[PDB]
Image (cartoon, rainbow, N blue to C red):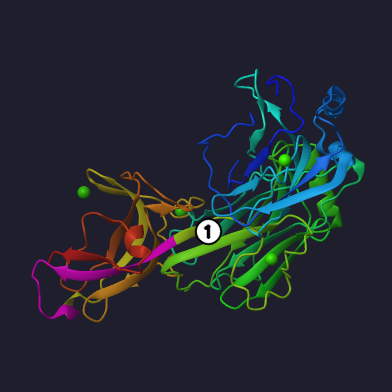
Amino acid sequence: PNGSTIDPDAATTLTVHKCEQTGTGNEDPQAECKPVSDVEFTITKLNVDLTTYDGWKTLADLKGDVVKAGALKSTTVQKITTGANGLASFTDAQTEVGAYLVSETRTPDKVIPAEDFVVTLPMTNPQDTAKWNYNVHVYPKNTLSGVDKQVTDKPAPGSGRDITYTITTSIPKVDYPGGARIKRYEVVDRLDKRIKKEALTPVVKIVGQNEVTLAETTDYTLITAEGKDHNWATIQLTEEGRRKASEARYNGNGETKLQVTLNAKFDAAVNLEGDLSNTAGLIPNDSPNFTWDPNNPGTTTDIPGIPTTPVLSKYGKVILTKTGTDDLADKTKYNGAQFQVYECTKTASGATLRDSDPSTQTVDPLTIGGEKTFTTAGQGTVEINYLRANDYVNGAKKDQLTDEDYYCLVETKAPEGYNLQADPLPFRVLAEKAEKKAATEVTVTDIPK
Ligand SMILES: [Ca+2]
Ligand SMILES: [Ca+2]
Ligand SMILES: [Ca+2]
Ligand SMILES: [Ca+2]
């Protein structure tokens, strides 16, 4: 057959590449693609004859409207489910010369669906416009740009202080002016049981170009529940909240998102040693595979819906040992020394203490586990429980550290027979110790009188 015109009896294939993150028709060997298995694609042949100019003209007239293409659907349908390599490889047995509507028709809960799209077999090869390409490769786009969770714990160096979580989730684009509405939209947070689930004081916004704040009851309701190994908080948009979201996204773009702020609170003496992990998930539609019931998590442990990566806060124990240049074997002589703790900047002359509460003129020490003063006892020791790692803050490792990234002990009362210190004493709590619940061991040496 002639190479320049369409061969009605040509063998064809259609290969859909399903990737976690996201069109020439040619295979693109990298092409960064983390393949996604177990996703079903359905192709439906359209009622256009691509062996005729009129068939191509019908497609052109759609001006890329995929919903209008749906009006051309035949009853000729084929399906394939991706394997480990994320490919849905429709064969020559499954495809013929013509146009197809391609839709992702089964999607594991955690996976973002592809957008529907139309493909032709063959395509004119843009890399060689003298060729008809009968073996088409397509890399579909995600319908949602992402879901993300952040933590702000820079304000919480001492354990038990407030931590803020911010969850930001894509909103599906639906045909708002046509009457289409998101039918279900829930943001679920899997809460560590150390957080007070009854005191989250949520704030919900639609962010992007021009942000708005949504109203509880009117636009959403917060539903919390006890769980097995965690507790649970769901922000569930109401009919009006869903309407606002549907509209905002339609008039906006992919970066028009819901933003949920949760204000996590603790008992002051909370045992935060180690990692405090938080994860959220998005349920973006009313598909029956999302069986989450915000009021009945039952024994669920995995986050429902499309998950964020977890975010961590890391708090460590400090064990302070008090001694002296006299090195007495009777360690009880080093009891009764008192200390307070600050964030500080190490300097050539010691350290500059940072005021823990800038609202007042007095330079205040940190409140750590509800306490400000730590007194040696026993064998001249005291535990300071617990301090957030200096090198892990706001949900990320601080790759580079500076002299600003310190805590300081200040000796506020010397043990009997000893001097106070000349300077504050800088130290760090490192994530490598805190995340393993390993103590940070600091020795303070006193000068005898
Ligand atoms: Ca065929
Ligand atoms: Ca499910
Ligand atoms: Ca000094
Ligand atoms: Ca102050």
What quarter of the picture does the N terminus occupy?
A: top right
* Amino acid beneath label 1: Pro
The quadrant in which residue 95 appears is top right
Q: Is residue 187 left or right of residue 422?
A: right
Q: On screen, 135 above or below 277?
A: above
Q: Is residue 104 left or right of residue 31?
A: right
Q: On screen, 302 above or below 246?
A: below
Residue at 33 percent of width and 45 percent of height: 401
- Nearer to us in this view, 27 or 93: 93
The percent position of residue 60, horizontal first and vertical second, equals 82, 25
- The residue where tag 1 is placed is 310
- Nearer to us in this view, 349 or 296: 296
Residue at 10 percent of width and 66 percent of height: 325
Label 1 secondary element: loop
Say if the magenta span includes residue 117. Answer: no
Residue at 58 percent of width and 52 percent of height: 36
Magenta range is 314-332
The percent position of residue 440, horizontal first and vertical second, equals 29, 65
The percent position of residue 418, horizontal first and vertical second, equals 16, 68
Q: Is the residue marked 1 within 8 Å of ligand 2, measured from its CB? A: no
Q: Is residue 248 left or right of residue 232?
A: right
The quadrant in which residue 280 appears is bottom right
